[PDB]
Image (cartoon, rainbow, N blue to C red; front, side, top):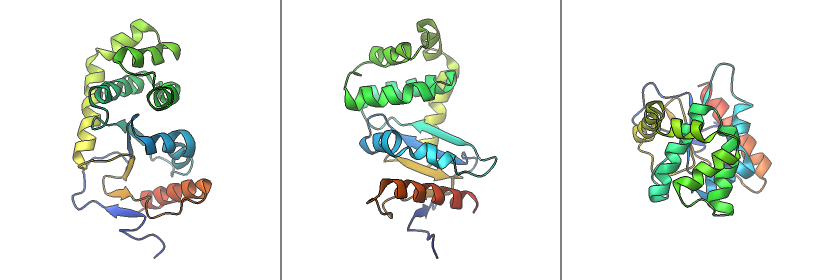
Length: 188
């Protein structure tokens, strides 16, 4: 066929019940994730092609970057709670990988402040139980699929994208193939 299990995607031998429809994992320490988000805009091009009704979820992971890696998972929880993902995603990636000005939890907090989130509001969220349960959700989702590398995308807890089975000569064309594949998997 044109789409083949084991080619553009794989099937989880152990499917995950109740999983989000489209689930992307990343780390702000992850070089290909920087490419995916900042250069390719994968999340965004997938969204523009997703069927009516199907929602998109993106979670941060702990297994890169040690202690700062976990801080970033908690910060990403704060980002989701406040709904400011689209304001902090670029400065967090650039702060970790481009300027390398993010070295502490306080430096992460600076990104939010500069983005216009109030200090008191950031700190309140950071320490909140709603954020703790959001950290929990992120951890559980990665655990459910035995996640050991990023970037990663899963459709309906059943299928995992396999971009290594794709031509990267042209980055526009790769992105649309990736997106068209997610759409295909979402209609399965």
